[PDB]
Every structure is written in structure tokens, then in C-alpha cells.
Length: 253
Length: 163
Image (cartoon, rainbow over all chains, first blue to last red; front, side):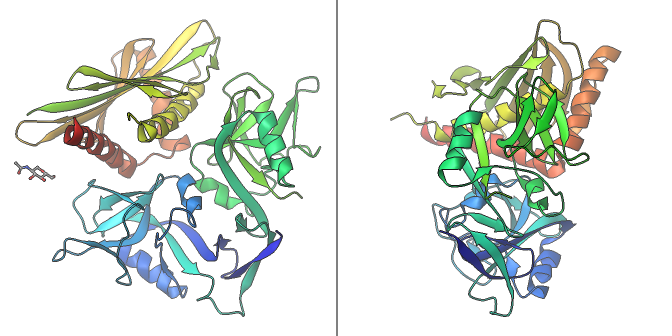
């Protein structure tokens, strides 16, 4: 496709006409809403599983724009918008009138004054044109700091996952920068990336020949094999290449 | 009127290599309810929620087992039990228990988030690895364990709601 993801704030995640940012600074809900408002935005509104399927891979619990009305007994978004069904599973965790988002489109009821991390979201249209455009990416790919990503939840072995990324004129995840790919901290589970062990040399290298940069990943031996699953907090778990797993493509460097 | 849901997920390592997949036993009021693995779940019976969630847990527990710096000698199993109870008076109990080669070595009460550590220093080593892993690598927090209790209870409710 090769389309520029539309007006977003600088170094926000831009996905399907929606800007996003994850704040790992734990504030309470109110503080978190104000924090998003101070960036001309608001807390995460979840309106569609399809347009916001990026949210399926998120680690941990994050304040979401959803609020409970004591009188109604209904859940509404910060701006008053109704919570559409077949989006969220509301779970009674704590007594409270706010909800933490967590993956598999779940929503844990939490006390609003409990510090938690948070997600701001704003639509591309409501950001003015004098603003940051995320670099050329395919249509339905997650654009973050000009790199393009997509997560394939249909699990395949390493080789097929490579070919899968090849078929979309991409390659498997190549980590080259903790700063530029700090998004990867919030990925849950593990996923095939393009890091391959050469058993002869005993080395690790990327799909395109590049050698693994030091102090970029922690490598843990899990399953003997010549392929590495990315896992969160920049880890690279060694896995048998024939083991089917989910995977992450990226437009190449 | 008192009910319980008991998940029991096992992951295995052979010569220190953590095996692919996992095996989960679910018990509903102590009656065997599901046996799940990587492929599917088995008791229009659809278990897409279970398969998703247990697979994710399988993945986590495999990470956890991989982080145990024990020995690469033979078979080892890491087994996590998650229990939640709804008592007659509507109160709950809930807990998390890890067995390594069938020896209980770590428990957390999910109502109180207090861990009970085992007596033997070996078992304690295992417990400390895993606790390290959970806190540092998995970055698990009180919220996660609140949520774990809630998940379990939500599922127990859900199952009670149908039959």
C-alpha cells in the first residue's frame, strides 16, 4: 500500500487513523485523564475490535477511558459515548468506578485513585495537519516512529513466518533500537522475530545478515533451536524453528 | 452452593529444554471439567476463550520454567495451580500454587497477595527463582494478581451461569 499514517503527535503509535501512546508512569485515573487532555487527546476509547486489534497484544493493565456511572449503573466513555457491546468483557476485580484495559479486550474494574499505567488515544482527524506523520507503511500496519509492524496471531513455524512476512514484502521483527522500538516493551506473550542462530559460528544474526547488536536483547535458553522468540522487556527466548508460534513482521531496514 | 474452579497447568522440560505446548486440567467443584493443550480443549462446544487464555498461560509458564536455573537432567515439570472458590456465604478464596516435580514449593493467596515459601532451602531456591521471574521478567504486580483472582472467579461464574 505504502500510505503515510495521518496526523499524530510526534512518536505516537499511528494505527488505522488513530494515534496512541502508552504511559508507563503509573498515575491514577484522574491524573491519567488530565495527562491525556494536556496532550490535546484523551484516555483510550475502544470502539472496534477490528480497527483496534493492536490492543490484543498489550501487556499489563492500563487505565482506559471507560467509567462507571453510579446512578445509571452503566459504563460510558469519558466523553459520554455509550459502550457498545461485543467489544469488552467487564470484570469485577476491585470495587471502583473506573476500568483498566487488558488484552483479549478485557476491562478490569479498578478503584479510580489506584495508580496504574495508561493509554492516551486520539483520532487522526482531530489532530491538526501541522503535526507528525508516521513514515510510509502498509495500510493496516502499526506505524511507530516510521517503522511498520504487524502481528500475526495465526501461529506458524519460524520458516513459514518468514515466508509470511516475505509475502507481504516485509521481514520478521528486527530489533535494532530500544529507543525507537520501545513499543515492544508492551507486547505480551512471545512472537517469532528474525533473529537466527548460526549453529556453526554460534552467532546470532538478523534475517538480512545484520549481526545482533550488544546490549540490545537478553537471550535466554528455553528450547534448544536456532530461532528466537521476542518476549517483553527486550528478551530473546531461544526456540526450535519448527515450533509454531505467533510472529511479528516489519518493513525492512 | 459452595463452588470452586481449579486450573492446573503443567509444562515440562527435558534435559533442561522446555517442551512445546502444555497440559491443563480444569476442575469445576472438584469434577474434572476440561483437558486442554496447545491444539484444543476437550470436556456446539466451543472453547475459544479457554484455548486462548490457557495457551497464553502455557506460554508464560514455559517462560517461567525456562528461567529456573536447576538442572538439565531428565524430566522436570513446572505445574501451576490456580484455584478460586465461591463459598456458601458468597465469600471467596483463591490461590496460586507451583509444583516442581510434584513438590509444592510456592503459593500465593490471591485474596491477600501473601506468599508462603517452603521449608527446604532447595524448595526455597525454586520459589525465589520463580518469584524473581514473576516480579522482574513477567513484571507482575498486585494488579495482575487481583486480575488473576477476578479472571478465575469470572470464569467460575460464567460456567455456573450455563451448566
